[PDB]
Length: 32
Image (tube, rainbow, N blue to C red; front, side):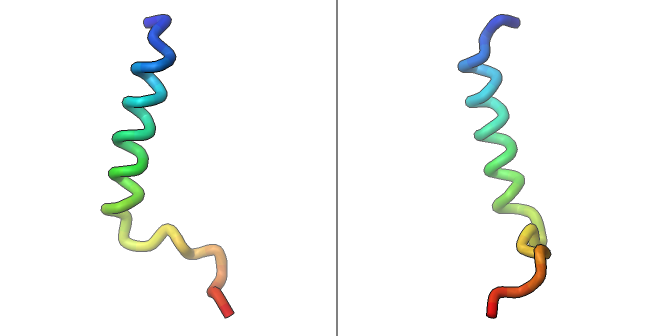
């Protein structure tokens, strides 16, 4: 519960892995 390390590692792991799988996050506009 008070396991901030586990929590943030868990997040970063899942979240960054999801970032990889996402179709396109880079929707902000377009690089010139």
